[PDB]
Image 1 (tube, rainbow, N blue to C red):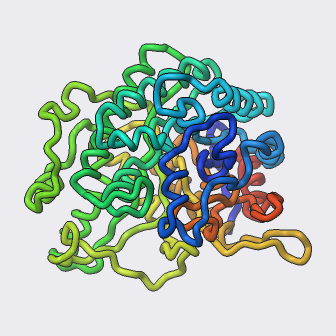
Image 2: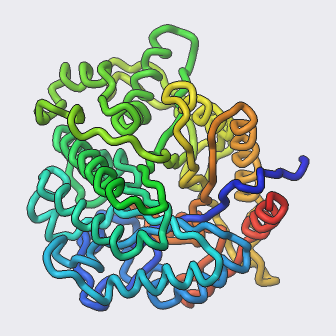
Length: 444
């Protein structure tokens, strides 16, 4: 296969989240988060794994920054842990927490790396969950105050802001399926949580615009192209319903300021739609500067009148990752072109794309992750083709910089381009990272 080359202004990065890599879960007066709570209760996370220590990045950040530099990576997406800054969610600011992020940001900049900051990446202070979490609109108000502080402290030096990571996952897995923190199992509440999360996004965007900083702000959505299992009208409609939940609910909300009417009807007819304020987003909608896309796989769907939204995913006979997710680079091309087709010319960033594989250090000290390299080659190829088709794709962040705590899956699923030995904390750059360094260099 021919070597891939992107335009010189394309942004190449890698991404992480605070809970997944930082550790130091109780240091410097950091408050308890919902993930600290969830992972400390048995039955929630595989093998009782937790983020207490994770990759110890809170301590090792200087060397981890040098790892990025050594790969020629010039953009780095990370999250700021709300409870390091406001241990109780609001009120008294924790200076040690702000100082950690100031030092990290200064370290990145000194080393020619542009920070992209995710403001909320699932680590709600537990004190806020004690008052309802995202079901309570008061928590959205506290979020904006927290965002305002970050803009004030860092906005002079940070030019890309992501308000929320994967609000669909946060609401659906956290409040409907009970598989992520806070572990609630109530779809009606999840839809309310999703509403308040979107409200907090638009309000943070509104606040950001007043500052006239040199930067851009947007949301990151997990998105998964849906295909019908057959050509029967039945199955095609089922795929469009799954698309409605997976993709359109948040796409329409974030990009048009409305929820898709077909899905409202479905949720209403099954009595899972919450009573939401009458105005919805009619008075608060704010256009983002970009849309962040987290893409990993597709869904193939058949009709099942007894299933949630009458849709059932079909397990496909194709190569798949250690998550069980089908490797389907065509889905990424299809998604990028679809977003440009349906929502017009808004700048796009792939804020996450990557794969979990069973990686390990070999007899020569190397981590030869050919499966990930090949995965990345095909997905970057699809992204490049979308660019050729005119999609305004401006950058691409690999998930993840290093192997980390994969939420309810624990440490068992390795997404890094850098291997982490959890017993010794040794980092070992994987083959895929070296391939990435060459891609970035070639494109520069």
